[PDB]
Amino acid sequence: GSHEQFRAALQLVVDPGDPRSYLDNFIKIGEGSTGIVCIATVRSSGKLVAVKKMDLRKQQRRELLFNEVVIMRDYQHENVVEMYNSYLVGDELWVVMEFLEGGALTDIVTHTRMNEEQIAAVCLAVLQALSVLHAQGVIHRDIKSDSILLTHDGRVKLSDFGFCAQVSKEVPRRKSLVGTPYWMAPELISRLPYGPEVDIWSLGIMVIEMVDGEPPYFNEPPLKAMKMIRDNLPPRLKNLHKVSPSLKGFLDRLLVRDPAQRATAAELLKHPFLAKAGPPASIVPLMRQNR
Ligand SMILES: Cc1nc2ccc(C#CC3(O)CCCCC3)cc2n1-c1ncnc(N)n1
View (cartoon, rainbow, N blue to C red):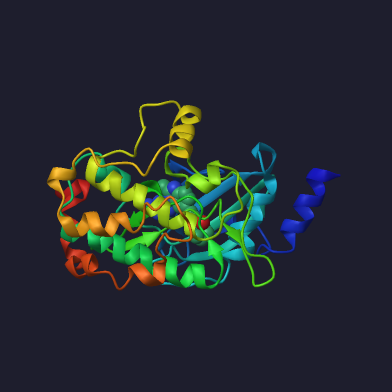
């Protein structure tokens, strides 16, 4: 019983019982990597939460469902979406978590143009979370604007660890073709054993998003694009002229074709460009209901 074995394994990691008993008023607010995301009210407290529901029978790699619940279950960090509980409901795994009322970064990078103070602020937060995460040996593996959620007061949180993986002192690196094509590191598309460095490349691609409004090759079909990324040199900004030398210098320590030469999260935190980072209040005017 393959399906049933997965259920039983999951029942060993999730909190027991039916969460529908204590949740009111479900409202769908998105699609995730592995399932859909709703918000609901906690009947007792009146609080709002977000709920990620993943169907066990609808997964390409069902084993990936252990990632968030095993790897992220206890995690806490100012810049990482906080998980509250997990449950098994019918054939679905549910993750109950913090609701980020500000929506995703994607909506901002496709509707406005961020200044450099705001860009560095997003970059600072993400890198802070990546430094701690990469230290514990957790690779996100799907960094992009969709994975960046905001609070009402413009605070930034890393999200959707549905594709994450674990590396250790005994086994660092993965050989897995995971992520979103346009944002994938070259050594990953080249099927090479890769480590945490693939997140830094991806953050670089997200910088291009914040500057150009889209990633490189975004018009090409995903299979073709991955090849162009695999074959060509580090991509160039369509708006290099709107960008300061500092941001360029920053970006250039991220889009290194050589993973060994690519900068690290811990390194990038000390970079001068991040001195431009503004307070979370600087982000607020970019959000939809304010613009
Ligand atoms: C809209 C949306 N899509 C999501 C996909 C994955 C995760 C996710 C996730 C996790 O991987 C984070 C780390 C703990 C385990 C769940 C969260 C998503 N949200 C969302 N969530 C909360 N608020 C808002 N506005 N939007």
